[PDB]
Length: 140
Image 1 (cartoon, helix red, strand yellow):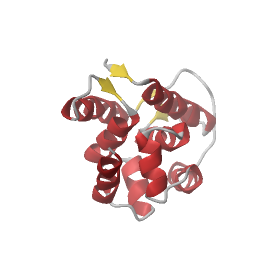
Image 2 (cartoon, one colour):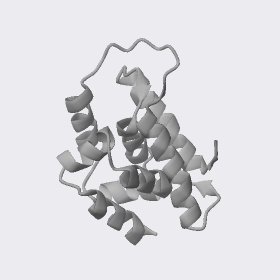
Image 3 (tube, one colour):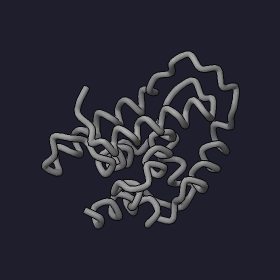
Image 4 (cartoon, helix red, strand yellow):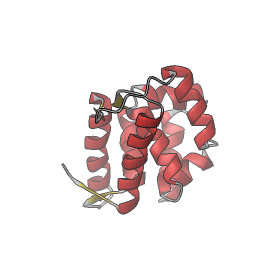
């Protein structure tokens, strides 16, 4: 589709690992969210840990929503929402002057799209989408 910073690519890679490893048939926004925080170094990760959301807090909440665990493996795909989040991320990048989607942009897109599991996770963990957007922007 578009271009991703190495780190964003890692976020999406981690999203897939998280999906696979949590044994979910699809990579959903929650997995992107996990990838964002797991990637660890990108603005998205920094924004998330600044928001008080470590991999574990998120991990736990994500599993509390989607449970586990029937791993299977057959190459999984993005949930429609995740696809949209990734589309949005491209827009977030564009709007921030970038031709490459970076972590901040996947997060911002995930926050803009703001529906689906990742969003509910943020909500469930006391982070409003706007506080989250606010933190990313601050970090930029």
